Image (cartoon, rainbow over all chains, first blue to last red; front, side, top):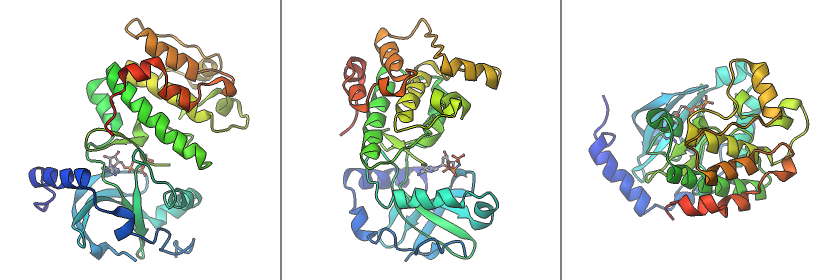
Length: 42
Length: 249
Ligand SMILES: Nc1ncnc2c1ncn2[C@@H]1O[C@@H](COP(=O)(O)OP(=O)(O)NP(=O)(O)O)[C@H](O)[C@H]1O
């Protein structure tokens, strides 16, 4: 079944936070091209 | 590097060409995003392998508040997982389906955010080529989001089989603007031949309800000769755009 954090109410409150007080994206998820070159199809 | 175990799958958001998009939350930050799950099998069985390579390298470089963000990506045996910025207000095409058409200030806002993000892309030597509602998502306060990188939306040169530059996006922007206010694309026909003849002759027929302000912007954007189409700068500065845009920044 669908988790509670994914349910409208407490989901809306969770979006507000990532909008108004946005976590540092490219810091936590740094290394952009990390998952190798074109050797991704095998 | 990431795996599917790093994320909490909450629920799906809708199918696509190559797989399902899920509402996800990476457990480390408890940070919400959208997981686009693609299947290697079909990706290969349709040769769309080349494009996927580019759409990733692009978002390794492109960062703009009006371009959908790809945080990262990974891949198990069977899939490629795209870590995409969550667009809370879903896609724009369905909003256009609901409302039938948008009012002047809604569209004018969309146009400034679009012209803006397009400019950013152009500076980095990146053309989009295909900008229609179906490729546009909406932020928490409704701000426009160019998501992924059709007859009605093809500029004359594209139809005629000539080489094209960045200016196809200027044409497309006009077509888009028109559909926003009217509800239908500007050169709609019941045959691909009639549409073809309408695009190249720029057979522009503006309905009675359209403001002269908007008509003008559209007319300047939808010009045959590419180098005449109003530059992105001229869009954001257009009287009707200035007078109607209400963007959150
Ligand atoms: N970031 C997102 N946030 C919320 N919903 C989304 C998001 N991305 C997609 N959806 C949902 O999924 C989208 C449909 O999937 P796609 O269009 O992502 O998959 P394609 O491979 O592009 N298919 P094509 O556009 O080429 O025909 C819906 O617009 C939207 O409800």
